[PDB]
Image (spheres, coloured by chain):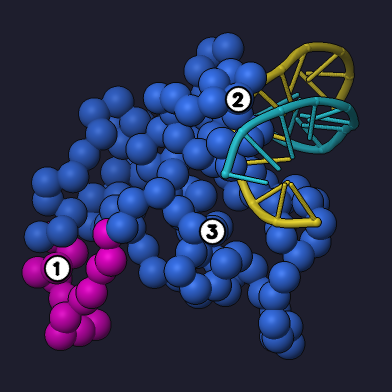
Chain colours: A blue, B cyan, C yellow
Amino acid sequence: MDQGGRGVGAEHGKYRGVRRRPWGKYAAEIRDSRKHGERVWLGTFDTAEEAARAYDQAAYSMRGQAAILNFPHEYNMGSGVSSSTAMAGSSSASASASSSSRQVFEFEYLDDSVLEELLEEGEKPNKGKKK
DNA sequence: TAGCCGCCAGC
DNA sequence: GCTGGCGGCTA
């Protein structure tokens, strides 16, 4: 976690789950508790705030419960299935000026969300249980 | 500009 | 040993 980072910095402005290149591009990669450190690449982001979130998805997936991530936002949607109010309300007003503006990925961020609930992307039944 | 690699390093 | 992130060559 902070461990890999100390050379650049024990703890600093950029987030956990993040790499920095000379141009400044940011890079998403994860390894598995269970596969002994093999690396699969979740993606690549410019963005540091949604960075933690790229790792969010991945790491909700891996721990399984009480996932180890920065921040605490929990989201509940009601009543539905039919929650246009909650999409629009939670979304507005959340924005990053430089990154979201790249275009098209505005559409996917603008309706939702900021923090999402996903389940065991990491495991394939049958696998009970992890470590 | 991006990805994979490889040591190494703090929790 | 955990799990990231440095880290810098090559892809």
Q: Residues within 10 Å of mark 3 (few under 14, many from 20)?
A: many
Left or right relative to A72: residue C5: right
Query: Which quadrant is home to the N terminus of chain A?
Result: top right
Q: Of the numbered discs in the image, which one, if any, rests on residue A6? A: 2
Q: Nearer the viewer, mark 1 or mark 2?
A: 2
Kind of residue sitting beneath label 2: Arg
Q: Residues within 10 Å of mark 1 (few under 14, many from 20)?
A: some
Q: Of the numbered discs in the image, which one, if any, rests on residue A86? A: 1
Question: Which residue is at 28% across, 66% downward?
Answer: A74
Q: CA distance from mark 3 to mark 1?
A: 25 Å
Residues indicated by labels 3 and 2 sit on the same polypeptide chain: yes
Question: Which residue is at 48% across, 48% downward?
Answer: A54
Residues indicated by labels 3 and 1 sit on the same polypeptide chain: yes
Question: Is A46 placed above or below A104 here?
Answer: above
Question: Is C6 placed above or below B5 here?
Answer: above
Dominant secondary structure (helix, strand or loop) of the stretch shown in magenta: loop
Q: Which residue is mark 3?
A: A59
Q: Chain under label 2?
A: A
Question: Which residue is at 10% across, 60% downward?
Answer: A89
Q: Earlier in the sequence, mark 3 or mark 2?
A: 2
Q: Residue A3 lies in what quarter of the image?
A: top right
Question: Is A25 placed above or below A49 here?
Answer: above
Q: Secondary structure at mark 1?
A: helix
Left or right relative to A21: residue A105: left
Kind of residue sitting beneath label 1: Ala
